[PDB]
Length: 512
Ligand SMILES: *[C@@H]1[C@@H](O)[C@H](CO)[C@@H](O[C@H]2O[C@H](CO[C@H]3O[C@H](CO)[C@@H](O)[C@H](O)[C@H]3O)[C@@H](OCCCCCCCCN)[C@H](O)[C@H]2O)[C@H](O)[C@H]1O
Ligand SMILES: [Ca+2]
Ligand SMILES: [Ca+2]
Ligand SMILES: [Ca+2]
Image 1: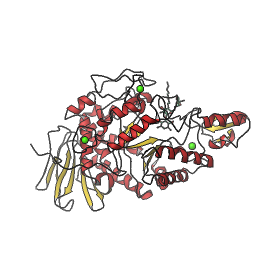
Image 2: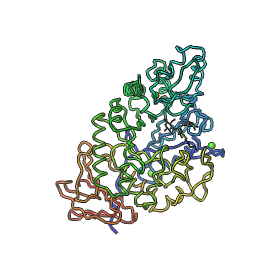
Image 3: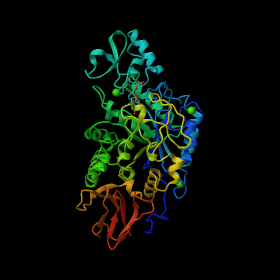
């Protein structure tokens, strides 16, 4: 019977770089034409589920940016081997379907970034097939100049290669079908400028940049390359946004931020062995708050405009729900609150919001299962390596979960609404932790210019925490928002300076 503190509070749609992102593995999301392959028209058909354009009404998820996995011609179902950087794979649609998707996203306040694969191309990209022919004729000063082609003996020993003619090879860390670009090449830079402009001119808001760890090599400074590319794209589109996958230690992420790239994925906090899920299982609130503050701030030293990119899991990892669901739905809910209420831009993986699991932990295809909009009418999508038979989410599909006020999905929805009511959360920096003499409680102050919030998480699985909020912490403290997983009907309150934070709950404190 305690009033919901967010009732009637005005939400505002984001109009800047700060977004709750949604990663769509295109193959697996929505099939509009019966071939068992997801496509762009399928995404279009579900845009009102993603964002209906009105932050103050409706039953949409509410995400305000999409990251599309590769959409360009490729023989593979994942398409990270790019055969043509200037078109749409026919299974996904045409450039007209792409233009429709952009228009329809933007009408709803949804930004769109593309997976732009700069480390490597397909071995069937025509630029590369020409290089291969020319190398076989001992011509190295044509198309070979686009690619990381050298005599075999040049390569660092632990570098995998593609064998070419006449004793030459091409760097290929990921596959024999993924030859690497020479990022130092004049010709390559020219080509990348053309590809960037091609997509930016179609209304794209920016890029996800895979495999940044492999920009740097024996002769390439990846920071120099990414700075060159990023600044090129800023000239084309001043408010272009990029997020890099740099799957490596913190010091390498610090280094790469000197490029001025907005964001790099925060791998440290992802997966079952990562900070967030590990500490939700271990009930380590205080540790998690400390680690988020220290990491966000360290990265800001390298780039003062860094936008951290928190995530539980992506298309290259086991689904987060494989670890979290067996710990109870309230653990899954807390996890969402923790990663999404950290500074920066969180990335929800499609289907995470309804608890899609991986049927096995070892096969990448099992990380990319079929999105379930309605568990009564299961999808019919083929995913190479796991077939087309759909798993049923424990909580049902989108339609089921939207109706149930206590669903995982509705918890995500509420998190997003709280963010749309409180811009400081995404845009600010953590200026300090707040101790509550309890290792289960993780609390920190996020401040964005003139405005500070106190975010408190109770990681305890079983125990409510009665906390005292003083004027030294937040002057004239009020309860701005709550997230209480046990029941959507349950709210708390701040009364005579005391607030009960239930198990696995989050509260947000703000000055009157
Ligand atoms: C970022 C990218 O950098 C990375 C590489 O492009 C993406 O990963 C994708 O590509 C790899 C490699 O796929 C290619 O090579 C494999 C291995 O030879 C071929 O099998 C594929 O057909 C070819 O496209 C891919 O890795 C799959 C490895 C499978 C191992 C199975 C072993 C057990 C067998 N019983 C990824 O699945 C694909 O996404 C990455 O996703 C980007 O984010
Ligand atoms: Ca289709
Ligand atoms: Ca809405
Ligand atoms: Ca490389």
